[PDB]
Amino acid sequence: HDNLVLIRMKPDENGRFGFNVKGGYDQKMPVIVSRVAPGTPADLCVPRLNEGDQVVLINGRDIAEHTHDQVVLFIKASCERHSGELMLLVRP
Amino acid sequence: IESDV
């Protein structure tokens, strides 16, 4: 819960971010960014979202005891975006 | 399992 980076990104015209997430409570694995595809919002935002980053918060929500499907639903919950941006707190 | 967002 230290050396954390706050990442802010707006989605594309199709409402996608360009990253993959693996893990969650049900899989007994931490939530990890498995891919960051080129030229996408997760690739072009500064600070950049990187592969291997562990997701800690999504729009301020603690994901520790949440299932993989709940994490994905949190990412897609556009109404929870502060000023239309998805906020992530990650551990590189 | 990994999901595309």
Image (tube, coloured by chain):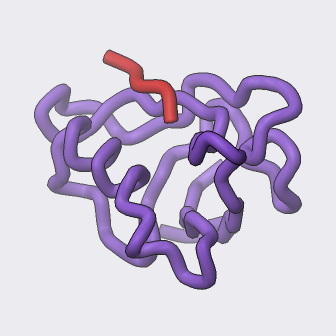
Chain colours: A purple, B red
Give A84 or A91, whichever is nearer the viewer.
A84
Answer with left or right where residue A17 lies relative to residue A77.
Answer: right
Percent position of residue A51, x then y: 67, 31
Percent position of residue B1, x then y: 31, 16
Q: What residue sits 46% from the left and 32% below the top?
A: A21
Percent position of residue A63, x then y: 29, 58
Residue A3 seen in this snapshot: no
Give A72 or A31, whichever is nearer the viewer.
A72
Q: What residue sits 87% from the left and 60% below the top?
A: A46
Answer with left or right where residue A57 lies relative to residue A19.
Answer: left
Q: Hey, which residue is sitting farthest left in the picture?
A: A26
Residue A22 seen in this snapshot: yes
Give B3 or A83, whichever is nearer the viewer.
A83
Q: Is residue A7 above or below residue B2?
A: below
Answer with left or right where residue A10 lies relative to residue A53.
Answer: right
Q: Is residue A58 above or below residue A51?
A: below
Q: Hey, which residue is sitting farthest top in the picture?
A: B1
Q: What residue sits 49% from the left and 26% below the top?
A: B4
Q: Hey, which residue is sitting farthest front in the picture?
A: A13
Percent position of residue A56, x then y: 44, 60
Q: Is residue A61 above or below residue A78?
A: below
Exactly how many numbered labels are in the figure? 0
Residue A78 found in image quarter:
bottom left
Q: What residue sits 69% from the left and 61% below the top?
A: A10
